[PDB]
Image (cartoon, coloured by chain):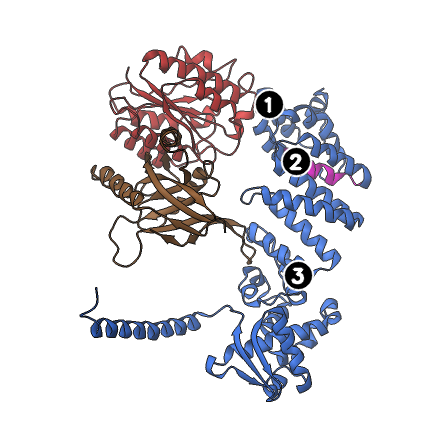
Amino acid sequence: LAVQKVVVHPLVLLSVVDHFNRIGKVGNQKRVVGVLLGSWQKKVLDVSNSFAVPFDEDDKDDSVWFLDHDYLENMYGMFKKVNARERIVGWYHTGPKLHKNDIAINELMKRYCPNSVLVIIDVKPKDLGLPTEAYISVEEVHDDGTPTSKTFEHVTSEI
Amino acid sequence: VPGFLQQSQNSGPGQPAVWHRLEELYTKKLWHQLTLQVLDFVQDPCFAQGDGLIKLYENFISEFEHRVNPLSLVEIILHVVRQMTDPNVALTFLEKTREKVKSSDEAVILCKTAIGALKLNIGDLQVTKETIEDVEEMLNNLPGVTSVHSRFYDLSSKYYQTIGNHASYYKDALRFLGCVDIKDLPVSEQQERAFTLGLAGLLGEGVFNFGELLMHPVLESLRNTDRQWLIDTLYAFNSGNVERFQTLKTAWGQQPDLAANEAQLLRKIQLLCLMEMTFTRPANHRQLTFEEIAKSAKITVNEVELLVMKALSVGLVKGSIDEVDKRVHMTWVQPRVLDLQQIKGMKDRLEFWCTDVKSMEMLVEHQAHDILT
Amino acid sequence: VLESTMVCVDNSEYMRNGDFLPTRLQAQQDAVNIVCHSKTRSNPENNVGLITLANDCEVLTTLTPDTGRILSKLHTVQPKGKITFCTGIRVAHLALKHRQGKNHKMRIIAFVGSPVEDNEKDLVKLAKRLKKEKVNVDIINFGEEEVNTEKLTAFVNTLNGKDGTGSHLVTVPPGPSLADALISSPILA
């Protein structure tokens, strides 16, 4: 695919943990979503920074969810002023597993980066696996005759 | 200009009340809400056959077409051109129709589908292929599936059926059945489509995944139909039972296409018999004697090698042939659809595998406990 | 007053109708231009943003103390899909929950020009949920008010409860321009 390996820096992990903790201080939340900035080296992603964006969703309905894309653009500009070589390469969320509305959020993010990568970062200290699980959106062409849909193809993630 | 509407208000081809409702919608300028009533009336249960609705185009919809949904503007013209039958001027009609609706790519897709179907009717397969290959590329750019996909898939399936390319016809018929709920289709249409899909799957080139086809709900429309033999034939293809195929010859030979391509059908079912033979045996005993393949596939021994060649060339199975010992060392099979009981057996194999992995992990942890970090 | 508003513009198919001169889409464009300007001069710190009400809700612009970008977004708004009023209001409420300044007050402008295809129970429960968070949703009942005059009635009655005119149900019968009825409505007062 367009992505061969996603390298997530420890700064990204610490930023994600801090974002989750500061939002969860409110005492009523499930996951937090932010934007991932990095560079491109051959076909290996180099996710190196991140910033939190306002985000909310309904507990019952998956189609109801708000993401502040204007905030996304403004903080992208602010970070680009500091580091021009770090560009939007995808997004992240701290939900332990995927969500049904993750495809819609990736479609929203794809405008800023066409080959956006979603890195699910589990804040909970899993004993065996890496905290990061990288996915990229692909058009799955089924052979059963079912119409082509958008799915998340997994990508080998490294720290 | 609305004089036609006022004419039909008193002396109308349809019900004057319907024309009054259309007049009220026009006066209120509920143009889109006028489009639903126009859709309801265009498929008229009274004068769909009469040519009067043709003048509905120029008199009524041509005046307000500048602010109609192109996708909702096109299918009205589909039934409008349904009435007219003159071939060549229909092409210009639909060309102008395609020209006016340029903002919506779906409208262009539907217009090209209509012109492709009409050109398939006249037998111009060469230009129909070019139109199909262009509208397919345009359809790929369209995100997701919409209401226009089904018409495209039907047109392309009919094109491949007219050519006779069974593989592509089966491929596209699967898509068509995938973008349309089967409950909406008539029972006769479902039965006919299931019969043709099974026929293409039998006659298609490289169509070996009969397990997925067998689970298609469309075939369920033929459970009690007289064409149930076809399902049985597919069963004979799924298990690679060439003896079942020869027994069912008395039923499937009556179909002209199966009778014509019985040789290719026999070759395909022989390949599937090879797949079944390698699949049944456990991985320790996947060395099939030449006699076993010859007896199972109802072929001579000296031909067995050639059969394996095909199965090796297509990619159905992997392995090698030891002709000196007259054996076939099969090492890999095309994965097939498994029953729930087979899945349970696979889960039991996973249980044993997990037990072994856990036992060895505990052994390594215990033996190297002092040096483990 | 120091309040934040989010306009629930409608871009359904029925906006193509010429009931409101010149078209319902252009009519609601002018109405949005008027209401956002009114909210801007009401308080310079006020926040405005655009949420569409298409087949699937799409937040065109979040809250911002700017006006021209709202009309810039509305210019590209094409009429497509069917109204989805249930999800649009909750999406807007989620947007207001994350305003730049929490001292602002809740407010949603709703442009309903298509029938609401939902049961009354969902609407009343949504109204109660918004009332719990002190959310005021002002609804313009143009377009198909002949069928929506009852569901929106229950919505506004349950939102406002028994005291206080937190939200209004300004119903504009078809005419020259619904914006010309907005400046006399309590929405802009």
Secondary structure state at the residue bearing disc 2: helix
Chain A's colour is brown
Q: Say whether residue A9 is magenta.
A: no
Q: Which residue is mark 1?
A: B24
Chain B's colour is blue
Question: Would residue B37 be seen by someone viewing this image from the given angle?
Answer: yes
Q: Residue B97: x and y, percent?
A: 71, 33
- Which range is magenta? B73-86
Q: Residue B255: x and y, percent?
A: 72, 68
Q: Earlier in the sequence, mark 1 or mark 3?
A: 1
Farthest residue in the left direction? B370
**Residue at screen point 76% across, 34% down:** B93
**Residue at screen point 65% across, 81% down:** B305
Q: Is residue B240 above or below residue B136?
A: below
Disc assigned to residue B90: none
Q: CA distance from mark 1 to mark 3?
A: 52 Å
Q: Residue B121: x and y, percent?
A: 77, 48
**Discs 2/3, front:** 3
In terms of image quadrants, where is residue B88? Answer: top right
Q: Which residue is mark 3?
A: B167
Q: Amino acid at mark 1?
A: Glu
Q: Amino acid at mark 2?
A: Val
Is the magenta region chiefly helix, strand or loop? helix
Q: Amino acid at mark 3?
A: Ala
Disc assigned to residue B74: 2
Secondary structure state at the residue bearing disc 3: helix
Q: Say whether residue B79 is magenta.
A: yes
